[PDB]
Image 1: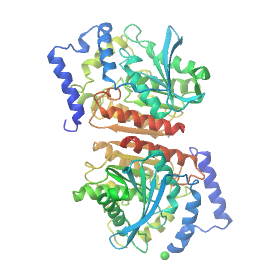
Image 2 (image 1 turned 60 degrees about the horizontal axis):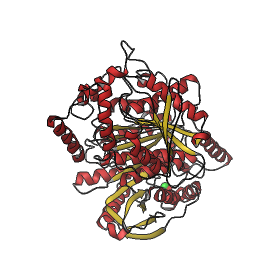
Image 3 (image 1 turned 120 degrees about the horizontal axis):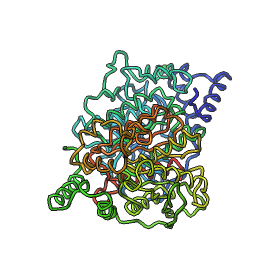
Image 4 (image 1 turned 135 degrees about the vertical axis):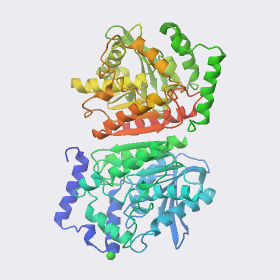
Length: 317
Length: 317
Ligand SMILES: [Cl-]
């Protein structure tokens, strides 16, 4: 509690005041009902959307449905084929969408001078595991196969995301390597979930009072994962991978008071020791979700900028 | 090993071609004589110097001599007071100077949109320990207390350096912290030496054949460190510090085949554990000194950009 930043404590205080005021916790609601309510809050939680050069909306055929996408063209960039980040929003594979991370994607685009393409994958409980990560993989594969159609440089096609979306990005890289196909050139992991098989110290220590609670994580899990599923499944627990060689250069960010902190850092450790170019950063005194809670948390904007800057430097923009 | 990048292999081959070609190795020359020869090579080893807005040369009164400096004003900024990186060149406190790292500082300035001030501290064997670091500390203190005359924003004053210069930057932060003084807002540690008391696994594994050899390190040591100096001295071994709290946000970079790799990463680890905002990156398959050997190693240019981008994003430029 002592290492908590004033802006972080302030937001938590506001949240606590709201709950005691009468605002129902998300885990007490039906998933579809709760989703609609919290997604609007997530939208309002972002900073004002910065202007970009161009925003495109469309969809393509996924494995079992249409997958909607949104492309963001960075200001000042005139090239036809841009280095491109495929972005997967967070929300426990249950909530969130393109709109909940729209401002964040906009800023990432401008700051990195890379195109950003946000993906609207299928959500649980309507489409449980492995449907969401299947869409994520299909989305990368489709955009890769049709890079020029998406205004993308196929040699510099990155994947990334926050939390659950960070997990998805991480799994996409592993899935491609294991399949023996060309994978992403870069992975941007923003406090990703990497281990569903065991509880780290941060998972236990930050179970309550830090926005992302254990009760909420259980609420997510009950919709995402069917009864009796192997928790060591690499699509659920990419951290447990036996081989980390052959994975793309990485940016891995954690938050100091995030339950997912330790397993994020451990994922970075595996990449480093495998000889993969890896950039790891921890933002102390902030919480899970700060990357897109940028109406309340300045640290999130700083994290946006560093992540974009590192990717931008990697791709030489 | 097999993880060596092709550009890294080519440079190492050029060096051993020159050695058996007749070129005497640095550790077989008197320090003064060897310095003149290697500095020219260090200058030539840099990429072509990019244009900047303005270059200033001057000096101020140090503890025991005049300390020369070079200010680099970044292109496109043109504000009165800029976020500033105080930079200390590398060379084992024996060789190197402002000229050997000129092109690098220029790129750092432009990419980060921060002013860079390169410090020409006293060198061994003419001025052994603790003279070189004493100048480094005095350089920061003087600029900090005279920020406006150095065109610097006092609230955004960083220190940084490569190798020996990286060590200096780290020590400056500890010194100010321990003295209760206002220290740097940021530290950029490019493969720093952090532990002179023990030989890490990387120090043993990469002791020979990777540009920075054990023979060269011992050659630096005899000029720099006087007889029976306590090797656990924190000015020689900042990694051994018992307290890491109160230190500024950091960028720590290591190279995959650097003897100093392990202790560099350990220092970042200590910072992370202590709750300091810390960005760590390892560049696998490249060597010690690649950050400024940018005529031969393009990885160095990427390293320049990442370091600059991280500092820029931290300072909000
Ligand atoms: Cl339900």
